[PDB]
Image 1: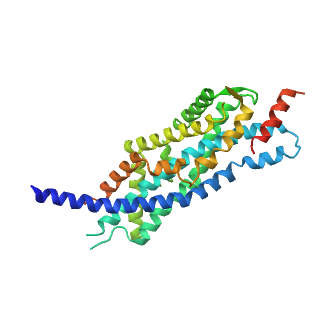
Image 2 (image 1 turned 45 degrees about the vertical axis):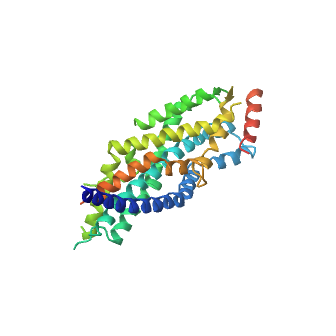
Length: 285
Length: 17
């Protein structure tokens, strides 16, 4: 009757206030971490140093340019992957822990402040060892796709999309969850609970629903990479002219600013639906 | 001794601007 309907209404309403609050937190955490992701990519894929050498009358000028060919494409390709992973991994973690935090409002507390801290600190991996492994793999893939391609080779916008698809296919069949968490290995009483949480996160990253939502974001991130570059094709350009167009994409793919790619992921209703389902699974007794 | 390449590389170096 109406009593049951009121009961389900209040439960949903309660779940929804905490979920929404938790999305606001997650949105903040994503945007505060972006400059660190951006800094790590620039340091590990430093185009601007190679450029500096070229603007300084060097020998092996073509070795530097071939290096730039790889670094530029690698950096923009990795910028898209890591940004999408950043957003979706934080949605997972914050709604997994949010779920537990929601339930502890009912003797034994499952997720106290120290478990929350040690669990959330696992984001480390994506910005750390995971990112470097990701760079190594994308760099190899770019090296296979663009290695034998001349700097004079003129590429149309369609050719460039096709190179990007080839890079993607080498990467995504080399899952992507290996880059977001450290491997599980073959204790302290709240380290037990932390291990249970990291395992549940790993399982989630291997779920079809998670893989679906990450694929959506990736698709939209690479279309955007291409839309951004379309403005420079007004026709085909020499690959050497494409390098600096591609090289500069990191600044927009990893911008905190509104209307940029990260904010479109944060306001993308498909990722919210996925996050809401995570929170619900982990907040129900 | 590749003029066309040297032109191409000089002008593309300005495109990082």
